[PDB]
Length: 191
Image 1 (cartoon, rainbow, N blue to C red):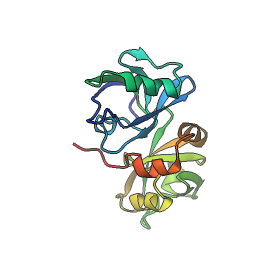
Image 2: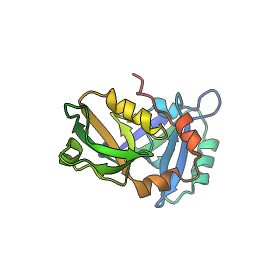
Image 3: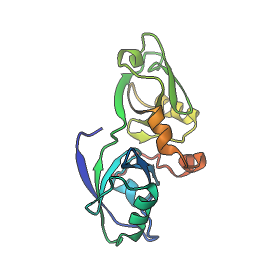
């Protein structure tokens, strides 16, 4: 999780799309969904990013409906956003034991217990936190088993990006679980 603002510059695709759903949270605007192969994934927008401005207008106090209407009406050519990096989230680095375990139990992407004397214990992983990213790959909406697969087929260093469950649940409210698995960009970014 970077420490400052960044500016990003999008262009709507052929279909006048950018691949973004936004959510009003505590009088700010946050990224709820980044669509695979969209302008918003190509420029590197993430789940949980805060949008401070759209085309130099402040988003403070906008409804989810208004932010969406603003993106709709924008002159396509070039949209500028001022982004604050995933401010509700944190990154923990752990190391698999010789048995390949980092040392937690999770259910519906939510960490529920920390195993005694694991890397997860030594690194202070918390329960009641949703897993957002593993090794910078977004896993929101994947089945628990696919999350285990990504952990398995990670090497012995495992970086996990987590969000307190109350905040997570407030962000995904009103978005169909099926859109999450289907359309939430789960890919490793392109170079």
